[PDB]
Amino acid sequence: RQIVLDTETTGMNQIGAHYEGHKIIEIGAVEVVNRRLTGNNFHVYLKPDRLVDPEAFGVHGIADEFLLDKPTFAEVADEFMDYIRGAELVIHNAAFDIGFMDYEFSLLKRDIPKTNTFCKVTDSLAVARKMFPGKRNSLDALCARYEIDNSKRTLHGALLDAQILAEVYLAMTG
Ligand SMILES: Cc1cn([C@H]2C[C@H](O)[C@@H](COP(=O)(O)O)O2)c(=O)[nH]c1=O
Ligand SMILES: Cc1cn([C@H]2C[C@H](O)[C@@H](COP(=O)(O)O)O2)c(=O)[nH]c1=O
Ligand SMILES: [Mn+2]
Ligand SMILES: [Mn+2]
């Protein structure tokens, strides 16, 4: 199993641990088996209990009010782990999302091990950079390169981004 994943957050830090003090507000993950999308995905919006930074809002457009009635990371953590366990996670700039995931897992105080100890982690951005050195390798740049539709991506979304990356990664490794 390959799980193409993405997350949206309240923001990030430019110095020090990028996730410190921030929270995941959306998790989007899509399953790929034998190079085919299975359709069995994972998608949740989470209540951060903190405000979304303006810069972050400018990217995903997810309002603070929309998250008030959502589950907390603690409430979705078990099913989330059941879903990703043992798979190869494919993430564009993996260190970003993995950092946030392990951070949130650690706050649960359940002795949950690091994600890369129970999941294989593949950074699709590193893969793209290796294949296309000296070129633009953002997800949008890769969409144009592989003729993938990203017209509905004015604002970024975790599931939306994961789905697009899945198509891009399948083409990049096809
Ligand atoms: C592109 C970008 C993302 N982010 C944070 C908030 C987003 O929810 C999260 C998602 O990045 P993404 O395009 O890698 O899915 O990263 C910023 O804080 N500023 C930015 O300029
Ligand atoms: C570690 C890190 C993560 N990120 C997050 C926010 C970006 O939108 C996302 C990557 O977007 P991109 O691979 O589509 O250009 O990852 C950065 O932008 N810069 C960084 O240095
Ligand atoms: Mn992302
Ligand atoms: Mn995203």
Image (cartoon, rainbow, N blue to C red):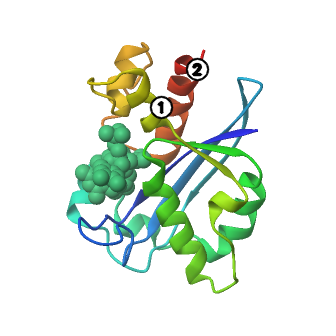
Q: Position of residue 169 (x, y in %)?
A: 54, 27
- Other residues around mark 2 within 10 Å, as few (<14) / some (14–19) / many (≥20): few
**Depth order, front residue of 154/55:** 55
Q: On the picture, is 143 further left or further right than 59?
A: right
Q: Nearer the viewer, residue 54 or 86?
A: 86
Element at label 1: helix
- In which quadrant of the rendered view does residue 9 lie? bottom left
Q: Position of residue 8 (x, y in %)?
A: 42, 55
Residue labelled with disc 1: 127
For the residue carrying disc 1, how many other residues have a C-alpha within 10 Å: few (<14), some (14-19), or many (20+)?
A: some
Q: Are marks 2 and 1 in contact (CB under 8 Å)?
A: yes
Which amino acid is tagged 1? Answer: Val
In the picture, residue 71 is in which quadrant?
bottom right
Amino acid type, label 2: Thr
Q: Report the front residue among 26 and 123.
A: 123
In the image, which disc is placed on residue 40?
A: none
Q: CA distance from mark 2 to mark 1?
A: 10 Å
Q: Position of residue 167 (x, y in %)?
A: 55, 24
Q: Would residue 16 be seen by someone viewing this image from the given angle?
A: yes
Q: Earlier in the sequence, mark 2 or mark 1?
A: 1
Left or right of residue 75, residue 150 in this image: left
Residue labelled with disc 2: 173
Q: Residue at x 58, y 57 (%)?
A: 44
Q: Nearer the viewer, residue 32 or 121?
A: 121
Residue 90's place in the image compared with 50, above or below, is above
Question: Relative to 127, does residue 61 appear above or below in the rendering?
Answer: below
- Name the quadrant containing residue 141: top left
Q: Secondary structure at mark 2?
A: loop
Q: Looking at the picture, does residue 25 appear above or below residue 174?
A: below
Residue 73: where, in percent of width, then height? Answer: 58, 72
